[PDB]
Every structure is written in structure tokens, then in C-alpha cells.
Length: 112
Length: 262
Image 1: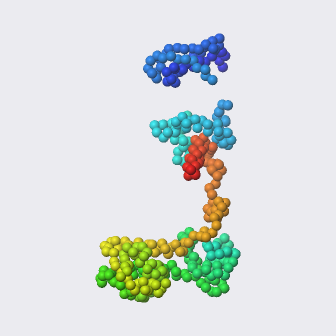
Image 2 (image 1 turned 135 degrees about the horizontal axis):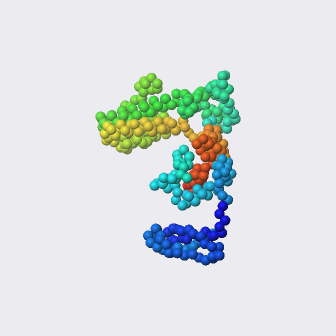
């Protein structure tokens, strides 16, 4: 287990391409904003990158308990809803989860 | 069924000697009123296929009156006779041209039920239409014939001063019209045997209607109970995608119901 105190910094592209780089900085510079000019493949040249603010665990045991008893189904229903709202299960050009279930009611294929 | 004629005090169905859950084929219906029972006894009861297409025979215990078990087939014969009468009259008009009503009507004959003996055509008309004027004025016979001016007394006098004229048709059109007349008379026959049981009765609450339905059909079991049948061998019980599909279907159904309401 690492004992380093260095802070993790994620530099997001200012071109709004969602591209990012990752590094670390000293704890003395917590309030110092890092900025760099680095290549962005989304736009195919060097743009600015800025550090962002970056404001329980669903484990295998909890997943098994939920799927065998269904007493806290909302936790995973929320993830399904997020995927549905984002654009999963659109029937086309999707090898992973083209459909919510097959005709018989199974959630296949298994992609994770 | 028998509530259509009055207040029914009781209905009993005798069980089979060898199976008390099934019937031997006999039942007793006790009415509140003599008039209601007498009205009920007049016609036999035709049942659908799910009841083995049986024709129930009725017998009044206080007067020996019986149902008319040959009503359906006698009416079928009457309908055939009416079609034959229409064809005969059209042929007579095509041969002799326009004819007066009181002379044309005497050339038309029917075949009696069941042995088909020739008779003067006056019974099929009154069993299928009620009168010669009804026969002429009811479709599709008004597309074959045209009555023109030059109670029973009124009928006779009114017919004594008419001439029947034909509508010039081709063979195919006339044949189609005859088939249509047969079909419409068949529908008329079925209506009087399938009169609705809620006729002239007050509306029933939703709970009462559900109780009526439950005698024949059971509602689907709750889906929450049903989900447990998904076998662990191939399914993950209480699966996220499956439950979300259920929720989406419920939302769609509620939206459609809201649209119907609005």
C-alpha cells in the first residue's frame, strides 16, 4: 500500500473534447491550478489543459444479495436508468448491450 | 340467461351419477312469476361451441308447455323460401313484364318444413318480414323490385292498386343480391337467439362486473410473485435490465391510459 501524500490532478482539455491527462502535485500546492499546453487528438493539435475541482461500494457480495433477494434493487436500477438516459440499448451498431433483454428475458450477451 | 324474463328465485343443476362435479344434463329453474316462467318457456336455448353447441329444451311443470326445438331450422327453411320467392317474382317480371301486385303475389309458392311440400307463399314473408310491404321495403329486395301506385284490410287495399316493376339487373348482381338477402336474414335469426342479457336492466358497478368476469376467467397473477419463477440455472433473478423493462412497459401503459382519459 503506497504511503505517498501527493495529490492526484486531472487536466481536462479546454477544447471541450473531454480528453484528459493525469499527474500528481505536492500537497503544498493544493490551491495552485495547473495548466499546460499539450496535444489533443480530438482537435489534432496543442490546446490548453486545466486542472479541475473533481468534487457505498457495490461489491460482488452485495450484487449477489440484491439479485437473489431484490431488497435493494434501486441501487442497480439507477445505473440501468443512467445508461438508458445516456443512450445504451439503441438496437443498432452496438455489440455490447444492443438490447435490454433477449426475447426470453435474459440480459445477454455478457459484455463486462 | 333466465333473468331476462323476470326475477329468478332459484336455479339448480342435478349432478352426474358418476361425477358430482359434472351435471347429468338436467336443471330446474324456479321463477318469481307465472307470466315470467311462461314467457321463458317459449323458445329453446342455443349454446355456443364452448358449451358443446347444445340446444337446451325447456318444459313448464305447471302447464306442460314445451320449447320450440325446431324454431332455428324452420326459420332457415323460411329464409330459403323467401329467397326462392324473390327469384320467382323476378323471373315472372322478366317474362310477363310489370304485373299488378294482387296478381303477381298469387304466382309465388314456398316449400313447407321439413318435407318441402308446395304451398302458397304467405308464411315465410310474415315470419321473416311481417308483411309483403315489409318484404318489398326491406333491403335488398327493394333493389330487385319497385312498388308503384297506379292493418290487414289496409294491406289488401293498398296492394290491390299497385304494379310491381323490376330493377333491371345482370345475373351476377342478382345472384349476389340473393346471397346478401340470405345472409341478412340469417343475422336476423341469430339476433333473436342471442339477445343481450343486460337489456332493460340497471348499470353495474366495476366491482360487480369483475365478480361477473371471475365466474369465467381468472386475473393474471401479480408480476412480483411471477418473477420468482425465473430459474437460477439460466436467469439472474431480480435482474436490473428486466426490472427496468417492466418499469418502462408500465410507464408506456400509464401514458396510453392518460391519453385515453384526455
